[PDB]
Length: 284
Ligand SMILES: CCn1c(=O)[nH]c(=O)c2c1nc(Cc1cn3cc(C)sc3n1)n2CC1COC1
Ligand SMILES: [Fe+3]
Image (cartoon, rainbow, N blue to C red):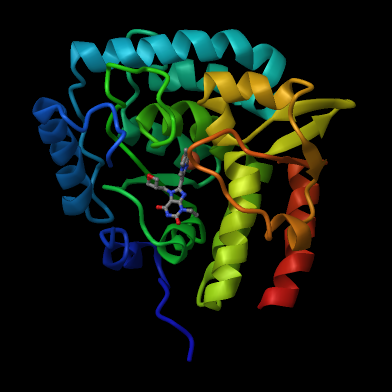
């Protein structure tokens, strides 16, 4: 039988709440209490609420600032044109600055106008099925906390810096928003195996994707765009690159503690969208 899946945007209320050891904040209680604070905001959020605005601490804003300054040095030569186009809009309308962490509510309002995408705060990891299902309604489940200040370059756990600098500029691009939504739509009520394959295709596009633009390789994956060292590595000659091809890409193991072994290159967001359309027919 078909598994339960959301049928309207408010149905995400029933799944978005269905949620380390080497972590830099593992032994810090103040950090743990703060993370509990953010988790509770997500857990208590219901669709229709304004996303609670948070007063970030001086330590958190400096951590953001450090990440923000280094990444911005690289974007002009590493990011795709769509990312570079949208990033200045975020600074002007959402307060993206070295000394200010943007509020999810402001970013959500920006995206709703541009592409109909919206943000929902998420306490932690959801199942692949639940996470993908939000995309079907142009809802991106977003972390709201900040990485521990002891290591501003600690990336294996996504934080709000990753969401705001990695994902948000692309969600404001119509072609990318359509591509993303169609992953969500394909996942709705799909088999467990199909959800795994879509989640892997998502991983090697939305999170670690490369694209070809005017004969050059650029980066569009959010995970790369928020990771200083891997952003450089991905466009270096040391990275292994292969064509995005869902029936192949969906078999690739997703790595979390190290650089990817391989990166997949999409011709464009429209082409990646077309390839997924052909692929999803065979798994659903
Ligand atoms: C389809 C796999 N998948 C899943 O199955 N469940 C999820 O909840 C989920 C998820 N992918 C993401 C987004 C993400 C992870 N990640 C790791 C980096 C390193 S960069 C980055 N971006 N999330 C959001 C949770 C992570 O904080 C909430
Ligand atoms: Fe991400």
